[PDB]
Length: 60
Image: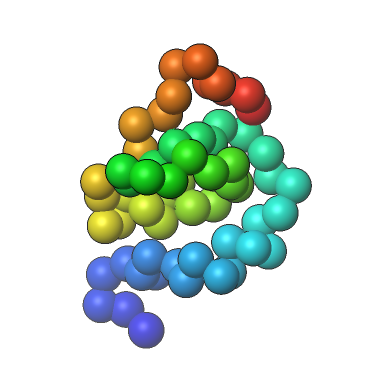
């Protein structure tokens, strides 16, 4: 569909990214949820979030 990128895949499509493990934690204020690395690239499109907790941590 162009004009530049993919662009920024739908979050429900990351559910197909089950058992991919790797590095995930926290998020935007009031989140604290475990996920798949699929969403790491998606959440960065809208930025903010992240802030991986040091005590977890990876947890790969």
